[PDB]
Length: 417
Image (cartoon, rainbow, N blue to C red; front, top):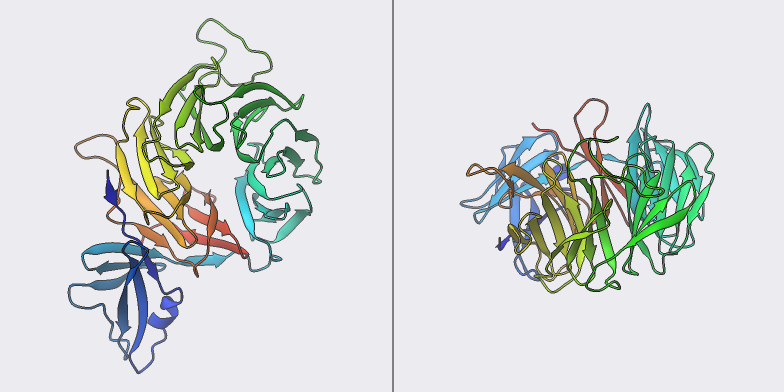
């Protein structure tokens, strides 16, 4: 707050340069953006004889893991995390705009395209089902229900659709949004879902009936479009019911739920899903759109919000008057997506930038703090991340899946040398 996270881009095939093992000197570049738009081109020489690397005086470059490299260049630290698997290998070419995963027994993946197609994939990224023309236009979001046996999609076509994983059937179509549906949150098992839209609404739906039972919006301006939503639990007790009194028609597990909404104006609003009260509004401190936000997975008092100017802010909902951290990433370039997983924040910036930022608890404690001085870049071939998906595999380890345009579907290892 306000400190800037220095972005580096490594030559995508640099690993092949390092393990080439040629007799002669070779070289790869690391471009460091400095407003960004301009840059410093660092040349890392890969000495022949496999006798190592020369990063220049005062600089280092080194392998710290099978798929993890560390550079220090002009006093800035960078980590570079390389692909462990291309998931687009056996897939027909689409521009991916949405992803989710589920694993009850078998692990599965769903992907949504700019063309409106949904693909169901298995553990090995082999196509298991294609739902062609699932929507008229771009799938903006895809979620499995917790059963793993159903899914919900959202689209520019202003509808949401519930699909069966069994047969690709479409038992429900949720209509009523007046603009693009941008986001989805599932309440508990999903008898209720929430959808966000550029029409300014967050609609609470009951799925059995396929109707909207409540519409939330920004109290100051109901037409301020919603880019992102996140659901959190205010308190983790106690249903049926440790207090008086209820209840609300056609609501299932809404009690103690709050929904956070990032707006086109850049404000953020928080709604008690049960009471229907707007509890909080965070100011558009940066005078631009809040494109994406996400809740801290350890402490839901803390949220992370990415804005159209490249500001990443951390807010404490208890103290809504000012952010508790501000971090510029390629100022002037939009943050497209922020996503909390495995004690880290994943951040898509502009057309080319994907960063994993570690979150620690502050020593002078104890409140989560972004490790902004030591970003990790998920190395691609100048590919654009539309969305991240955390894959805890079988047994509490993890990988991150990125999907994007031009058939980008790439897996990254998160665990440590």
